[PDB]
Length: 124
Length: 124
Ligand SMILES: CCCC[C@H](NC(=O)[C@H](C)NC(=O)[C@H](CCC(=O)O)NC(=O)[C@H](Cc1ccccc1)NC[C@H](CC(C)C)NC(=O)[C@@H](NC(=O)[C@@H](N)CCCNC(N)=[NH2+])C(C)C)C(N)=O
Image: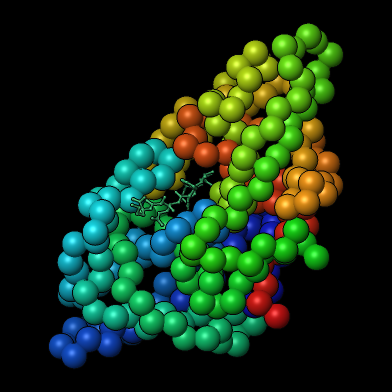
């Protein structure tokens, strides 16, 4: 990946998720749009994009906090496989994880994912 | 500036702010800490580190929405000069703005002054 910081355009990307849980779900693979968030410790998919059938459990800390304050957070129970699509077509490396889900206004890939993809923010 | 993204520790820089306004201030220059934030569109200095004796305007829209809800903002009257000292004291390029001011848990270097530093995310 390579993506110049532009104040006007948010570092937005195409992401395909895939529930790999040995257990049925209506749709194993979905499609979303997700901001690349460096001030985001964690990767959290909004509840309005999380499938009503993909199970969830307790996240270790009842909520996540940000600007306005804390927002309730639950965690993925199955391992989702997260795959990133670069603007031009190409595919970034597949990473697996148990995401956090909450009423986020946007799905954000936090520093845990950013790190897996091998991302350094640079002006060099 | 070339920060490799870890989930581990945050993209934090130590900054310098100078009130370039033609009016007395107690202290013109202050050192603060800040996080590099691609998910944030504006730079927002904490009410905590803002020497509240640098006037503000309630200007724009009391933005500051994030996963929390909304929070009031002010924006600096006087153009502020902002400098990114990296680990060595070597400063980056001086930027000039009118940061937004709110009760942010941390000072954010948003994309605007993030594209002014030339920062871009990459793994190539
Ligand atoms: C015991 C510790 C366990 C770990 C757990 N960690 C957290 O809660 C941590 C601190 N939270 C975070 O990392 C959260 C994201 C949630 C998450 O990943 O968990 N990050 C954040 O909230 C960061 C900023 C931040 C940085 C440091 C500290 C606090 C906040 N902001 C993310 C957020 C995303 C955006 C799409 C709405 N951006 C904003 O809040 C910025 N807002 C904007 O740029 C607006 N102008 C436009 C967005 C609104 N509209 C919309 N979305 N359609 C603002 C900073 C200028 C905890 N502490 O409970």
